[PDB]
Amino acid sequence: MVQFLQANQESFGIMALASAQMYSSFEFTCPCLPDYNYAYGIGILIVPPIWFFLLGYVMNNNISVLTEEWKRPVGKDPAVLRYMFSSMTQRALIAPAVWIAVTLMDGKSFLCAFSPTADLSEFVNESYQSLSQKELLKIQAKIPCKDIFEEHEIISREAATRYIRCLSQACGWTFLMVITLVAFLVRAIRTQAAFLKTKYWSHYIDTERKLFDETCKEHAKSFAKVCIQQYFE
Amino acid sequence: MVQFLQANQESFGIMALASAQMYSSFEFTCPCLPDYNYAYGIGILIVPPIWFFLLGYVMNNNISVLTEEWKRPVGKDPAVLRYMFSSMTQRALIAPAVWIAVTLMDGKSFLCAFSPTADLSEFVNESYQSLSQKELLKIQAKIPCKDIFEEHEIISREAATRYIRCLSQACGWTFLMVITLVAFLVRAIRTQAAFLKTKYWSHYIDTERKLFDETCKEHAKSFAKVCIQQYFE
Amino acid sequence: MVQFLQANQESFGIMALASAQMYSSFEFTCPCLPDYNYAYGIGILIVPPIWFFLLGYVMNNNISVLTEEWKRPVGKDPAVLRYMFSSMTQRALIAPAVWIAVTLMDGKSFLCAFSPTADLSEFVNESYQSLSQKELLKIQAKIPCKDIFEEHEIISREAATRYIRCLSQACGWTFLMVITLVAFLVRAIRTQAAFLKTKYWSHYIDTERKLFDETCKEHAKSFAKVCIQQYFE
Amino acid sequence: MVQFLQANQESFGIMALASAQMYSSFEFTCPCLPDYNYAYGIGILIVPPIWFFLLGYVMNNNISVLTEEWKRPVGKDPAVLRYMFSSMTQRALIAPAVWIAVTLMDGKSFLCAFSPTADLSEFVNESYQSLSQKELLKIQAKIPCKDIFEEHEIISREAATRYIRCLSQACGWTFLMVITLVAFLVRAIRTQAAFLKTKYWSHYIDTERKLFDETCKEHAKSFAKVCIQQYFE
Amino acid sequence: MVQFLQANQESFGIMALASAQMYSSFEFTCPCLPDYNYAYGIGILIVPPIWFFLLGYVMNNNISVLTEEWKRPVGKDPAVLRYMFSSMTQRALIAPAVWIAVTLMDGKSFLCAFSPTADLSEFVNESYQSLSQKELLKIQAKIPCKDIFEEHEIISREAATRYIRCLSQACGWTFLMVITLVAFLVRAIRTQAAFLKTKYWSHYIDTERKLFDETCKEHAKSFAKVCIQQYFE
Amino acid sequence: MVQFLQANQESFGIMALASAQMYSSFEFTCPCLPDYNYAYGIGILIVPPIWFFLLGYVMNNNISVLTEEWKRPVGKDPAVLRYMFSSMTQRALIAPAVWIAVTLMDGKSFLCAFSPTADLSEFVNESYQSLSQKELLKIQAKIPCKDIFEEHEIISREAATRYIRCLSQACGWTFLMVITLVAFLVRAIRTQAAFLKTKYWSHYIDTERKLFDETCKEHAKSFAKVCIQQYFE
Amino acid sequence: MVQFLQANQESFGIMALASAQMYSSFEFTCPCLPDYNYAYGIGILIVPPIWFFLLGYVMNNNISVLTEEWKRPVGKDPAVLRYMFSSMTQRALIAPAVWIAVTLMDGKSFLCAFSPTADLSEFVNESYQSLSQKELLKIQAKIPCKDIFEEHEIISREAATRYIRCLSQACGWTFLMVITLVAFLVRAIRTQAAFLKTKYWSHYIDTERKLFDETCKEHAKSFAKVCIQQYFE
Ligand SMILES: *[C@@H]1O[C@H](CO)[C@@H](O)[C@H](O)[C@H]1NC(C)=O
Ligand SMILES: *[C@@H]1O[C@H](CO)[C@@H](O)[C@H](O)[C@H]1NC(C)=O
Ligand SMILES: *[C@@H]1O[C@H](CO)[C@@H](O)[C@H](O)[C@H]1NC(C)=O
Ligand SMILES: *[C@@H]1O[C@H](CO)[C@@H](O)[C@H](O)[C@H]1NC(C)=O
Ligand SMILES: *[C@@H]1O[C@H](CO)[C@@H](O)[C@H](O)[C@H]1NC(C)=O
Ligand SMILES: *[C@@H]1O[C@H](CO)[C@@H](O)[C@H](O)[C@H]1NC(C)=O
Ligand SMILES: *[C@@H]1O[C@H](CO)[C@@H](O)[C@H](O)[C@H]1NC(C)=O
């Protein structure tokens, strides 16, 4: 909370804090069922970033012109469309990456998902060191559920929890490193004139809108003054 | 809380935070009665978005002109009325969608509603695996009520709670995805001149109001100066 | 708390947050007596909105002119008085409505009031299913008092509490819907020239006050400069 | 706390929040002694508003001129003194009223004061329904002291607490209503030229101070420039 | 905390909130020893206000000129020195008064100090109603120490605590009233020309500093422009 | 939290608060396994600063020109590249240093890492003063895990925790001192003309961008005005 | 926390709040070992102020010129170097003093340090009034460690804690008084022309930097306009 606010202050690239806060304000609840744990985990991992990607796409006020150009046979930039589309895509990819990083550093989804299948043989008590893995499926399935796990005589819930959480944090750090390296290479490589042409078209849109609102003002002023004569009368 | 404030800061499309905060500051209380659970759940789900829709309609300062035009036989735009009405409607639909999304991601209403009817056969203890569903109605009815559920010997309250809550979260995510796709398609499709005409009428209203207040100022200045002569005397 | 602050930020129609915060910062205490519960409940429900109505009336800086006009036989607007008075009244009605809505959504007053009389026959234990209603008066009277209700062997306090609270929330939602519909109809119906005339009189008041303060400034400047001569001496 | 800050934001008539916050940040401690309870209660009720009244008097920057005029036999306004003095008094009365309202709505002082004398015959256990009122004095005296009241076998502390607190809240609401009605009548009745004369004298003071500081500036500039010649040397 | 921030907002006379916050953020620890309780109490009461007085003296940026004038045999105001010195002193006295008021309203220091000596004969159990006062010294000495007082069989710690705390609050209120009355009389009595002369000297200092910085600017501009010629080269 | 916000306010050199807050908002979880404790500790110590270094590199908007110059055989500054590259590097080194300092002052990583190997012979109970170090490996491995350490009969967890934490704090203070001394020497030694040349190139970039956007504006204005003629038609 | 923020608001001399907040956000951990307690205490007392002193030295943007002048045989002020160096030193001394004051008023370091050596003969139980001081070393060593001190049958931890904490607070108050007196004397004594000369050199630096950036702007504008011709082409 305090951190997201601080990030916002620094900013004062905004959907990042939106995703972070939405994750922190989300009631994560592992169903703790052997048939659905994997589904729920991978779902929390995969669906929200997809939705964030779409949301980033729609909130961009120039998708309309992209569709317009992709529609015509030959429209009134042979390639700036590529450039502006790729810039929009790059802008959009921030929130899903942030969501994945956050949900991995906090090993909740990983714990929910890989709890039933993973091998925890050093954690299972030595007494029940020999029993059908189908029962261990049901048992380990309840591991991320504090109020439900009632087999302290068999498995230490806390040890396994810390184990899988460390695994998740390691994966999250590797993911962050890979993303940072890719971003570094991209900025170190990248296409010049298209940027100037899009700057031109942007300034064109701005001056068109401002001229239009000004001429609307001045042309409505005449009508206003004509009709306000009776208003005094 | 911290999240809503952050969203407001980002904004600095406002009723969204209003709806979110109103939900968070709402004492949700499932009656935990077999005759009314469904009613209360679906009510909390359906009524508040309807009220929010109406509220969005009334708070818009141009509904009056819409009624005026819909009233006359032929008024002084043959179709911009369609356009401005649809834009108002689109502006209004935000808050109900936000309310539904929030109340689904937090599986409270879903839990209250579908608790008595849904089949929880893996959760009911094996001892009472055979008993009239009418008794299970009363029993499962109390599931969302922590302080009231006194049948731990029959059903695990926590397991069923997590189950139905995961179901609710899944439904909420699907709803969010569908809404986002629909919004994407709408922005990718959509009617051009009507926008310019409404821009014209807006500028007309603005210049009319400003000219009126200025002429009121200048015409009252004469009276003020005439009457202030005795004020010095 | 966080919500009221957010509402204030959105605003930046102010007494609404005042009423909400005053309710949240109010020590509601049901006397839990069969003779006074009804009185206290309906009082908390009815008196504060009346006081808020009066407060809204007095804080409006143009009530004086309303009294002045209502006093004279024929004063220097034959009907704008109706208009400005009704606008003041409409401005004033916000806070009482907000108070009623808030105190109904939180079923405290309803619980305190209708606890002794209402019939709770499914909640009373089956053992004491037959006993004089006068004793049940005293017993149910203590229901909203956690620290005082000492008859768990007779009535479940929590079940009845949730029941009556759901009733209160339903009533509050119906009230909100009715108020919203009425507001929608009012804005959809409503008297034109009176608005312009009141705008004129307002601008007149403004220019009169500004001209008066300016002439006071300039006429006191002479005296100031005359007397400051000795100040240097 | 959150409420006082919100009130301050609305304001952005300031001593009101000062009094409210000072009450909230005050360690109220009922001595729980039959000889002093009444004294302490009425003291907390009466002394702080008197001090607030005095504080409002002194903080007003024009009390000096009031004393100056009340001192002379005939000073250089035959009656604006009445007007400005009454306006200062009205400004001052806010904080004491706020303090009384707050301390009554929270029935602490009332409870401390009227605990030993008031008749609580329905609350005293039936076993000790007959015993000298002098002992009940000592006993009921300890009622507002949670950690000290050790006679649960005789009197329910919570029931009596709620009772007297409801009484206090009722008295506070009546007080608020009376004050609001009086304010409404005052604004509906009230003396015109004195206001303009005080506006004149205020503008006179302002222009005198500004002319004085400006002439000080310009007359010191000469000296500054004369002495800065050696400063370069 | 919330109150100090509100006071700061109102202000936006600053050391007052500094003293208040420093008191609230101070680990008050009564040594609970018969030989040192009095010392510690009176010390916390007396030393911090003295230090605050000194701090107010030093932070004032015109003490230097006061020393300069008090040093010379006859300096370049025969009495404004009295005036500015007294105004500085008055400005300085705020923080010590605030500290004393705060530390008295919260009867901690009073409790620590007057615990061993004061007579608590109604609080001491009747069994030990006769024992050497030297033992009662040690016992009552531990009264302000919750974790240390182990004589519940002899003295009620809470009753005596409330007693002495009420005494402290009474003393604090009397102190506040006396200070307010003195301030009222001072403002109602008070020396005119000295104020204008100090206003003159202040404006002189301001214009001297501004002229000096401006002439430094302009005279360094020449050097800057002369040396920047090679900078381009 | 409160501290990071205060630092941000002081700033209003920003990644420092980012790193601090990210550490505070990080679920540190020592796997408490003899095979992985060292790995996890040193990883939390080493990886995040590396990632922060990379992040500082990429976020700098002039890495592109550095790559461009390092790419060409001879580009259009023979050495300012060294200067700007070193300044970027210096700017980048802040966040890793801050992270290391923070994670050392809070002896979590140190405790997790050096728990299994370090010799705690004064802390191990005297009964088990003679047992294979391989068992002590497993035992001491669980020391940073409160919920897991179940050998209070062998080792005091708290004593060893405080011991290793003091060691970590000492190391952190030495690190801070060394870094501060190095920074002092660097600022006391350091290359002059390169700074002016980079200032020149920066101003060049600024004026180029501003001239380009202005000429885009003016050249699009013609098109806008040409096409807005039909817009009125 | 709230206090530091308030201080920052008052300020809006900044490292003071930095030091205060850093102390409050520091995990103080007394090793509770007879061999190291003294070391840790005096270290926390002495090292951080030294580091703060160095930090204040380096953060000052004019240390470079001080080194430059101290380096040359005879540089281009025969004594303003003394003046600016002393002013920098005075600016730097704030944070260490603040740190010492804070860490003394909260008697943590004092308690950790002087616990093993100090004589607590009135606190040690009378049974063990005769035993080798070497054992009391180990015992009293654990006094500042709540979770570790297991000799309630020998020494009251709380009494000794309060004792040593009062000692620390007394020392802190004396330190504050001495520092305030020294500051008062310094301001009352203090070297005039050097201040004006440093003001001159500061204004010189400012105008040089501004002239340089302006000439860079204007000289790069020509190149920008020359190269933007092809940009339109
Ligand atoms: C293993 O199980 C036995 C009994 O089955 C129990 O006594 C023992 O404490 C268990 N050990 C662990 C580590 O769970
Ligand atoms: C099922 O019921 C039996 C007795 O009816 C009880 O002993 C057992 O613990 C119950 N099991 C569960 C899972 O509720
Ligand atoms: C009803 O009362 C009987 C005894 O009077 C008690 O044993 C039983 O638990 C009670 N049931 C409820 C639901 O209160
Ligand atoms: C009244 O006193 C009797 C014994 O004196 C006790 O058993 C009973 O519970 C008391 N009742 C109340 C309501 O205090
Ligand atoms: C007084 O002391 C006796 C025994 O010495 C004890 O039983 C009694 O409760 C005490 N009373 C009080 C009020 O402390
Ligand atoms: C050491 O172990 C013995 C038994 O093995 C136990 O009684 C004693 O309390 C232990 N001492 C410590 C300091 O752990
Ligand atoms: C002193 O020690 C004895 C036994 O050694 C114990 O009974 C007594 O309570 C102790 N007193 C204190 C004040 O620790």
Image (tube, coloured by chain):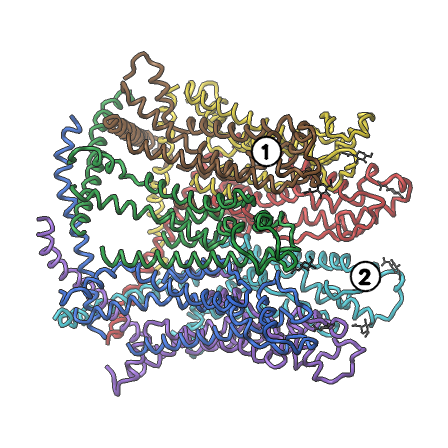
Chain colours: A red, B cyan, C purple, D blue, E green, F yellow, G brown
Amino acid on which the number 2 mark rests in the picture: His
- Image height check: is F84 above or below F214? above
- Residue named by callout 1: G112
Q: Mark 2 lies on which chain?
A: B
Circle 2: element type:
loop
Q: Where is residue A168 in the image (x, y as percent from the top left)?
A: 70, 39
Circle 1: element type:
helix
The foreground one among D142 and C96 is D142
Q: Position of residue G25 (x, y in %)?
A: 54, 39
Question: Is residue D215 found left or right of C19 in the rendered image?
Answer: left
Marking on residue A198 = none
- Circles 2 and 1, Cβ within 8 Å, touching? The answer is no
The foreground one among A17 and C38 is C38
Q: Which chain carries label 1?
A: G
Extreme residue in the top direction: G73
- Image height check: is G65 above or below E86? above
Q: Where is residue D53 in the image (x, y as percent from the top left)?
A: 35, 64
Taking the image in four quarters, ligand 7 sits in the one at top right
The foreground one among C91 and B150 is B150
- Residue named by callout 2: B152
The quarter of the picture where residue D75 lies is bottom left
Amino acid on which the number 1 mark rests in the picture: Cys
**Mark 2 vs ligand 2: CB below 8 Å:** yes
